Length: 115
Image 1 (spheres, rainbow, N blue to C red):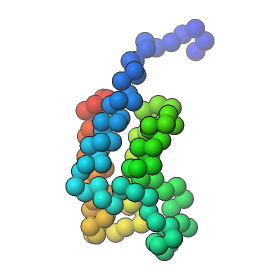
Image 2: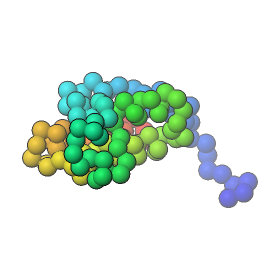
Image 3: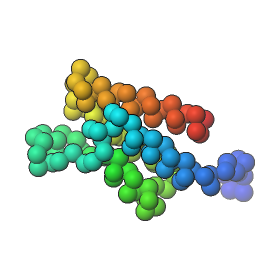
């Protein structure tokens, strides 16, 4: 509350560390469904169904331009990429399986870097 604060957690390396995680997600062999925005002219149903599209290149541009206020808003966009994928793709599909693999990969790196 006013003039009463918890001890200050050092957040000065968060930007660099989220960039490194994003680099590792970018270079994973199963990243290919997630590298670029879904083409809304060429994929029937996507525009109407997925209310907030997200992808790795859009996260990278947001990160690089100071559009993430803190490390939690960055994790929310990464998780959005996987939630969108589960909404649109069957579990038993190459893209469906890709999304589950990448989410697992991300959550481990997130815990090990920050928790």
